[PDB]
Amino acid sequence: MLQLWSKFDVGDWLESIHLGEHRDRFEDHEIEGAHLPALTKEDFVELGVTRVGHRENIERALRQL
Ligand SMILES: [Cl-]
Ligand SMILES: [Zn+2]
């Protein structure tokens, strides 16, 4: 589950929701499962998620879990 995801799982998760384009950068920033729920709009910008739609997809996917 989320809290137990390593940076690679988060990467796999991004692919599963069609945002694999963002996995390398997330990985370089050492983003792990436990970090996801706390990422702000600014963290996402810094992580390369500059398209509101994609940030919304990430956010929506987090609520599903
Ligand atoms: Cl984007
Ligand atoms: Zn994107």
Image: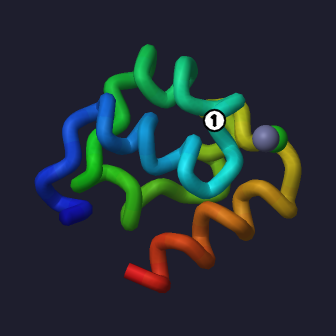
Indicate the amino acid at tag 1.
Gly
Does residue 53 appear left or right of residue 49 in this picture? Answer: right
Say if 14 sits above or below 54 in the image: above
Q: Position of residue 51 (x, y in %)?
A: 87, 49
In terms of depth relative to the viewer, which is nearer, 12 or 5? 12
Question: Can you tell which quarter of the image residue 53 is in?
Answer: bottom right
Ligand 2 is found in the corner quadrant, namely top right
In terms of depth relative to the viewer, which is nearer, 12 or 44? 12
Q: Position of residue 31 (x, y in %)?
A: 36, 35
Task: Name the residue rendered at 61%, 56% in the picture.
Answer: 17
Give the labeled residue for mark 1: 20
What is the crowding at mark 1: few (fewer than 14 residues within 10 Å), some, or many (at least 20)?
some
Q: Quadrant of the image for the N terminus? A: bottom left
Q: Position of residue 42 (x, y in %)?
A: 64, 47
Q: Position of residue 36 (x, y in %)?
A: 39, 56
What SS does tag 1 mark?
helix
Say if 54 sits above or below 42 in the image: below
* Label tally: 1
| Residue farthest bottom in this picture | 64
| Residue farthest left in this picture | 4
Task: Name the residue rendered at 43%, 39% in the picture.
Answer: 12
Question: Can you tell which quarter of the image residue 19 is in?
Answer: top right
Question: Can you tell which quarter of the image residue 7 is in?
Answer: top left
Q: Quadrant of the image for the C terminus? A: bottom left
